[PDB]
Every structure is written in structure tokens, then in C-alpha cells.
Image 1: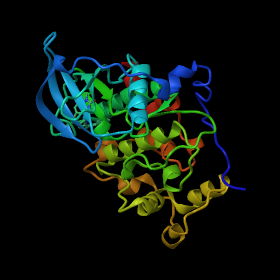
Image 2: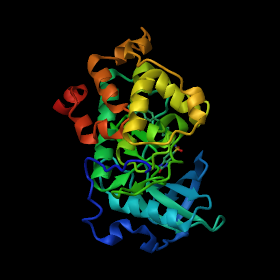
Image 3: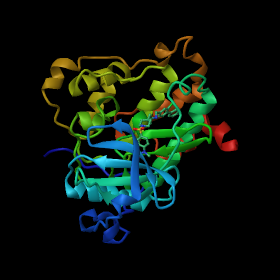
Length: 329
Ligand SMILES: Cn1c(=O)n(C)c2cc(S(=O)(=O)N3CCC4(CC3)CC(NCc3ccc(-c5ccccc5)c(Cl)c3)C4)ccc21
């Protein structure tokens, strides 16, 4: 009789109540701007689906970031553009400024607002407990916004977060895997980077929702507070879930698969074994202690749950005591 269905606990019906054009991205028509408005200055990054450059708009001498896509399906270009346009002006969401057709690749190039980006040497070294809480709050602002606007990011990870520490500014980037949440929809589980994949992806439960991003956030927090990047260090997708189970325990895992009547790939029964749920104190040492507090562990514990329906929402996360000092200020 197959897997038990699931719905988001929050922002369930938000896309239903919008006009079709908001989420029916296949009907979105893309208008091109002038590629010659932009001169490329230097390469910043190269990343599987795209290359990223710093550029100058010669029309007005503004500095800009250009993301030249590798060949992708038109429908996925339209989804990313549509989501970027829908979320534009929202808290800590990267701003799409223009879309042009590259003369060499004949592929699209997305043009973004420039955000100055501080080295991961200056940061991650005298990044204080306060700083982690502050920037986590800022990420939660972006996720609560995008979730409220009917959109899961599905690729939350440090590579997709930019911080300008001089200006205490943060941006969530790389919306190319984001999707619109619709109740009853089965999504592709072949998303996210392995270290950040939620258990639902790993056990092939397709009827997932915004709560996927909350697992990913949990991975990032763990990694920051225990100074262990990545926290769940799988050697492949099967072992990824073994790494998770060596911490969260197998008991809650088997309960999760029972509740949703999930069919476990029999590969997994050779390898999952039996494991205790571990106390978070086993990952605390003197070299990470200043980042770890009762309220951080309580928060982390409530993000990293197998059952996606039982993880904090972005809003609930923002209300957690971990953040009382940052909200006060
Ligand atoms: C505007 N624009 C775009 O749209 N794209 C695609 C673009 C691509 C580029 S890039 O390639 O030069 N490149 C920029 C540098 C990074 C990698 C990417 C490193 C990553 N940030 C790491 C990070 C992330 C999170 C944290 C953190 C700290 C505390 C609490 C929570 C989290 C900390 Cl401590 C660090 C950002 C540039 C502009 C772009």
C-alpha cells in the first residue's frame, strides 16, 4: 500500500492561494538585456552548473556579479529566474539585477548585485559565539521568508551563504535547486550535497517540504559549534545515513521508516546496524567549548530529527533562547 503521505505543517497552501503564474514557471517568458552592458573583470569561482565572474556595468559604472550557466534545461533556468524574481527584495535574498545571453556560451548569464565577501581566514578565526548566533539568525530570516513565499531552497550549505562582515550583511545565494512547495507533490531526492542531505532524501521519501532546509541548517550549526566540517562525513549516500545514525541512533531511524511505511533499499540493512543515540557532549572539546552552550545544543537537537514533521520551523527556530541576545540587539 506504499509510503504514507505528508504535508508541510506551515505555509502549506501558500502557492495554491497565489495566481498560477507565481509558481507555474514553465509559462514564464524570459526577456534578455544587453550583454554589452557588462564587461567581465575577473573570474571568482567555477561550480559544476556555472562560472561566476566579477563584472562592470559600463552603463553606470556599478560593480556586478555575473553567473554564466553551463547548458541546463530551459525549464530549470525559468524556475531559478522565477524564484529569484518572486523572492527579490526579501530579507537576505540575493538580488537578481539582469539576465543576458552570453555571446560565447550562447547560454544565459544571471547578473547579480555585488556583495563584498570576507575571506574564510579572517572569518572562522575569532568568529565569536555571538557572531555565529547573529549570522544564524540572518540565515533564518531568509529561510522563513522563502518558506512563507512557498519555496524550498534545497541546497543550504556554507558555499551558498555570503557574509560581508564589515557591514554585518548576509545573503543566501544559488537558487538553482530551489522549488515551489505544493501539498502532495513528490520531488526529486537527488538534490543537495551529500554532507547536507536530509534523511528523507537518503531513504527515498519524495513527499518532503521546507523542513528539508532545516536539517541542512542543523548540519551547518553542528559543523560550526563543534568545529568539524563536515559534521556527517559520509563516504557515499548509503554511508551518509550510517554517519547520521551513529549520532542520532538507529531506534528513531527505524521508527521514522515505520511511521511513513518507507521501503528501505536492502543495501541499508547490511550496513545500518544498531546504534545508540549519542549525547552531544562527546563532540565537545576545549578547542570548541567557547561556541557550545546548553541553548546551542538544545537548538541543534531540535533541528536534527529524522522525522521532518518534528524539526523546528524557521519561525520556531528564530524564537529559540539561543537567539535571545541577538533579538534584544
Ligand atoms: C553574488 N554571487 C552569486 O550569486 N554567486 C553564485 C556568487 C559566487 C561567489 S564566489 O564563487 O566567489 N564564492 C564567494 C565565497 C564563498 C563561495 C562562493 C565562500 C562562501 N561563504 C562561506 C561561509 C558561509 C557561512 C558562514 C557562517 C558563519 C557563521 C554562521 C553561519 C554561517 C561562514 Cl563563516 C562562511 C561564499 C561570489 C559572489 C556570488
